[PDB]
Image 1 (cartoon, one colour):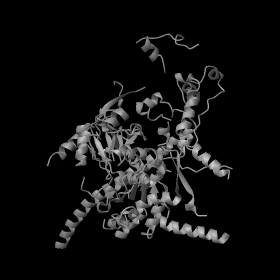
Image 2 (tube, one colour):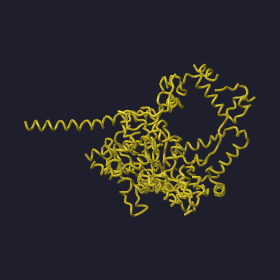
Image 3 (cartoon, one colour):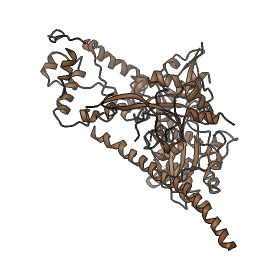
Image 4 (cartoon, helix red, strand yellow):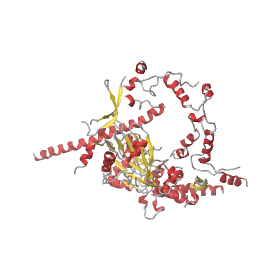
Length: 53
Length: 49
Length: 136
Length: 387
């Protein structure tokens, strides 16, 4: 499974592109920025097939 | 009593005036310090490359 | 390339880019495409005493040839060099040499501790805002 | 700083320079003009030159922004959609905004138009308007004497403790575009050629006039003074033996002819002399319209102690602008150190980045507090909509 290989690979936050409202308290506007996602926030080809040789 | 009353009214106005002066003074320092440190960090990662 | 490199307010970096013209891609296994591209660059954007005026002051010289001194930037137009010390890339060509410098960069930075150029997991713990922290 | 990705835009009189806060370079530097291709097609974009390389009939490079640094074609400037999508490739409604010429306090309106342009026309959820000569002073100085020789002219702005000396903000006429007219005028016999033509004139200002401009000069003294001094020097060198620096050829290769355009050193000096002495081009312009007595903007700043203003300005001179990147600052040092020798001219200048120094100052966006600048909410439009 692709996700099993992926979680088996490269061994941890997540991050989001979200509207933040900034603080001065909060501004009457808001704006997008990459906010920190917190803790609670397919198929395979075999290689050597596309290998140029 | 009259002169100390007038001085008491003079002091409050002076104190109120100073804060908005020093609000302009302290923001002048730190934003320039930010603009200095941005002018620092403009060159910092530059030489690393 | 002429309208790209002649619009620079810096008159000197224009010539240094003008003399390191690199043409890459899977098409660019074509021979002479880069060569006549360079020749057409010298045709369109090379600043010189032109053959009418350099011939005219060749004739003024035969009366040692001086040059009318121009002020513009693209006076020398050249290409750049490919590393011939990779026999795998000497053999399989340099049309996709972007992968070659990627291989050289990978042996550089990854076999180095330098995470000023790659995001770590802890660097993700700024995210892709640390992708803005790991650029070259 | 704070977790923000503001959009940093500098709108000069000729150049629209756009990128974000998290990129210290602009994503694009297109004109603040457009080849209105003729449908009307407001062709923004520098290379989109090539349309004006067609020199096409109906193609009309009108400016969006006149010589005051304020736009006169605002919905064709809403170029802003062209910026955010064709150049920035982002929604403006995502990101905050920093946008950059000083005035006397009257047009403080255009913000309402930016309330149009950032809330109604583009719906940028928050936009900060910064002062461009004050931004040039920022990128870490508090007070300055900013002279921007941009495309619009010589724009002099005194700045005392961050406040704008409103009576002393003077903007000259004579900068990039008048020198485009000048280089088109004087090399006219040598180019053998001699807005709508902005497709001829702006295109030539993109191809060869700039190629004579970044390659024009200013005399470090007055050119009449340098001319008499160098003629005296050459007379000394000739009479002692039995060379003038001004008799040498600065030939120009007019690439639409590939032809030698021999203008001398004094000849290329004479164009930028009109920025300090515009009586040499037309009688309706005084030497006061030149950059030397523009001294007057120091003196009008003396009324905000006037010698303390002189101390601050003439020891905190700032040089910026596109036409100031024409060689010759030392003209400013000479020309204002003769009108004010009292405080020695300790000048500051971005020397490269100078033509986009308002963009870099607006980029300094990357302030550590949203409270350091006025960031306009949609509610700030709603407050300005009342009374």
